[PDB]
Image 1 (cartoon, rainbow, N blue to C red):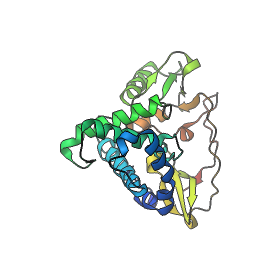
Image 2 (cartoon, helix red, strand yellow):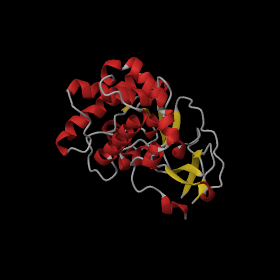
Image 3 (tube, helix red, strand yellow):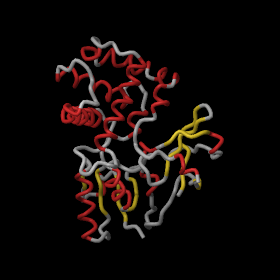
Image 4 (spheres, rainbow, N blue to C red):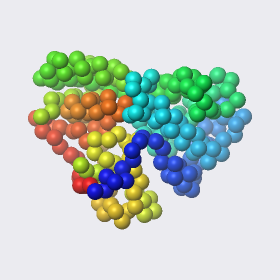
Length: 270
């Protein structure tokens, strides 16, 4: 099986982040930060690789603090896709800008994401990071509509999961991000660099996406579906989110308007 090399944790792929292309991609992030979060980054004058290392520290912190192994975490992991958005006004810029703004506000001499004494203030930073992403339209937490056919006892359990993971639920399908239907081993390649291919493991969150050698994955990378409000997924999308403390990839759980599972892209067996 290829699941041999599946990540056992949602920690950062440090080699991807230290790679020269990624360091190069952060250049526009550094420049954008210098213009719009200037009073918070001017002192530290972060280089491209310093930003890259900060991303590793940030990703490692939320996996250590809010990971699958943590019973009742104080917070839910930020989506891994947020850290993959290197565009000028994108999510990664607001992530780093919020981190530097928060550090300036607390008067910290430096980031210390390994200090157990600073756990609660580091959690506080991530809350400020999530708010910055949401209020700048880079992140939208699920606003969930439960199909009325779901058993009331299950629906109430799903409602508690949704609230414990920064989500809300609504009674008007008009404004729901997701519609949840009753529900009655593979991977998918998502990115290719060098001889490395990033693969997504079915029923695992995006932080568990693993860089593997392209010769072990002959499958073609297909185009991700374009988002049309709302996602139609079944209840295991919410149930699995509670397991990993990280909102699952909707593609793995999608159903059509008759509750039958569908997969826009191909599923490659492990």
